[PDB]
Image (cartoon, helix red, strand yellow):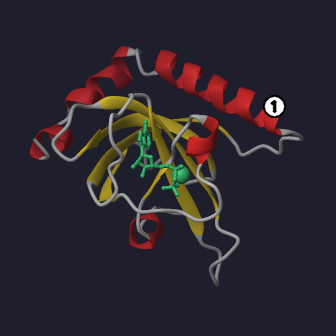
Amino acid sequence: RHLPYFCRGQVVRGFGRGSKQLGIPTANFPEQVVDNLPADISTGIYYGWASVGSGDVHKMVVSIGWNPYYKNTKKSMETHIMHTFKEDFYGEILNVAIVGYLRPEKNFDSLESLISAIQGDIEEAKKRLELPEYLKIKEDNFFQVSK
Ligand SMILES: Nc1ncnc2c1ncn2[C@@H]1O[C@H](COP(=O)(O)OP(=O)(O)O)[C@@H](O)[C@H]1O
Ligand SMILES: [Mg+2]
């Protein structure tokens, strides 16, 4: 309904143990960004395009979830980019275009099932983003402003 959704924000650290531990780093935005998401934004896994600062546009998956820790029902958002970066990019601006929904949130009974699920989400996202209707979003002026 509110896709494609375009947003930008400073990349900020999270809490607990980072998903770098799984080889699947997930970048966070400040609360301000997540708070401006429409409500028709469901929790779950989405896919789209991302660039960092003035960099090239790459495929990405975004997880939108509920935040346990803030008062009121606040959400969380974290983006894994399907690109190998040589350096972290904290403080840089992440530009995202969320283009499609993959699945609702699910409960997993082990890290093995979780990690397999995440990997499968990434492979599915890669395939779907080849569809001409989504492939074109890579070229949106949204991403050209940041270069
Ligand atoms: N492919 C990538 N996708 C997302 N973040 C990446 C990627 N490569 C490097 N990073 C870096 O990894 C950080 C996220 O790591 P992570 O372990 O999830 O910690 P945290 O969530 O606390 O920031 C990002 O802020 C960014 O600096
Ligand atoms: Mg993370």
Instruction: Give me the residue at 78% from left, 43% from top.
Output: 106
Q: Which sits in the foreground, 141 or 108?
A: 108
Does 121 appear above or below 101? above
Mark 1: which secondary structure? helix
Instruction: Give me the residue at 27% from left, 28% from top.
Output: 138
Quadrant in which the C terminus is drawn: top left
Does 119 appear above or below 24? above
Q: Is residue 40 visible?
A: no
The crowding category of the residue bearing disc 1, from other C-alpha atoms within 10 Å (few below 14, some 14 to 19, many at least 20), is few
Return the x and y of residue 13 as percentages of the image width and height.
46, 62
Number of numbered discs on residues: 1
- Residue furthest to the right in view is 109
Q: Is residue 52 left or right of residue 44?
A: left
Instruction: Give me the residue at 63% from left, 37% from top.
Output: 22
Please identify the quarter of the rendering in which residue 122 is found: top right
Type of the residue with mark 1:
Glu
Please identify the quarter of the rendering in which residue 134 is found: top left
Q: Which sits in the foreground, 143 or 14?
A: 14
Q: Is residue 122 left or right of residue 28?
A: right
Q: Is residue 105 left or right of residue 141?
A: right
Instruction: Give me the residue at 34% from left, 15% from top.
Output: 132
- Residue furthest to the bottom in view is 71
Return the x and y of residue 46 as percentages of the image width and height.
53, 39
Please identify the quarter of the rendering in which residue 121 is found: top right
Return the x and y of residue 62 as percentages of the image width and height.
51, 43
Q: Which residue is mark 1?
A: 112
